[PDB]
Amino acid sequence: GGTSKLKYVLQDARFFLIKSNNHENVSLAKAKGVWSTLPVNEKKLNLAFRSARSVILIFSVRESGKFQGFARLSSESHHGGSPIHWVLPAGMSAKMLGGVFKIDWICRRELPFTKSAHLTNPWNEHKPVKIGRDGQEIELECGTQLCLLFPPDESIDLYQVIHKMR
């Protein structure tokens, strides 16, 4: 129903864990529909955006014990546009995060790691899906089920994110 529309968005997607060292940038991403990541992940995501039906980013603040939501990647990274002043972690320069992706939030509700305890990611040595570095790719079925575990977000029109797929 709502689950059917979501299943359509997730069909044949590639799934990536996104980690943030702070809460602030995830809130900023929720506010403005943008994300930046470090250089290896930026190339990985640009390549996936071009080749995959959908690219899904599942956000988790480092040490928060939760995921904070997930979103569909809606562009490759754009440089030299209107800049985003991210909250940089100690030792991270603004240039390390260069390149801004547009993203379309699907769910901005939290999912505690306890609710994902039955899911392991075979593409990360079969570790619980809550374990992974920034950018860790999640196997299709594991990633699909992780997204379907999140509560419905009644402020996100899932008809609208689908329309945006053109």
Image: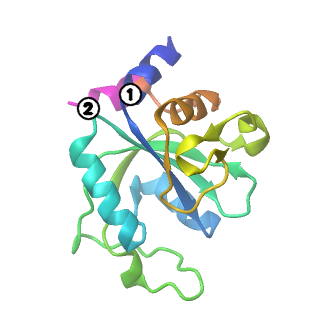
**Residue at the extreme top of the image, as rendered:** 1
Q: Would residue 148 appear left or right of 13 to someone viewing this image? A: right
Instruction: Give me the residue at 39% from left, 64% from top.
Output: 41
**Badge count:** 2
Residue 13 image offset from top left, x and y in percent = 38, 35
Instruction: Give me the residue at 46% from left, 34% from top.
Output: 140
Q: Tell me if residue 124 is in the magenta stretch.
A: no
Instruction: Give me the residue at 57% from left, 41% from top.
Output: 122
The quarter of the picture where the C terminus appears is top left
Task: Assign a secondary structure to mark 2.
Answer: loop
Q: Nearer the viewer, residue 132 or 147?
A: 132
Determine the CA span between mark 2 and mark 1: 9 Å
Instruction: Give me the residue at 46% from left, 24% from top.
Output: 6
Residue 134 image offset from top left, x and y in percent = 53, 62
The answer to whether mark 2 and mark 1 are in CB contact below 8 A is: yes
Q: Would residue 162 appear left or right of 80 to someone viewing this image? A: right
Task: Indicate whether 159 appears above or below 99.
Answer: above
**Residue at the extreme right of the image, as rendered:** 114
Q: Is residue 128 at all visible to an observer of this figure? A: no
The kind of residue on which mark 2 rests is Met
N-terminal label among 2 and 1: 1
Residue density around tag 1, few if under 14, some if 14–19, many if 20 or more, within 10 Å: many
Task: Assign a secondary structure to mark 1.
Answer: helix
* Residue receiving disc 1: 9
* Residue receiving disc 2: 165
Q: Tell me if residue 164 is in the magenta stretch.
A: yes
Give the residues drawn in magenta, as a range: 159-166
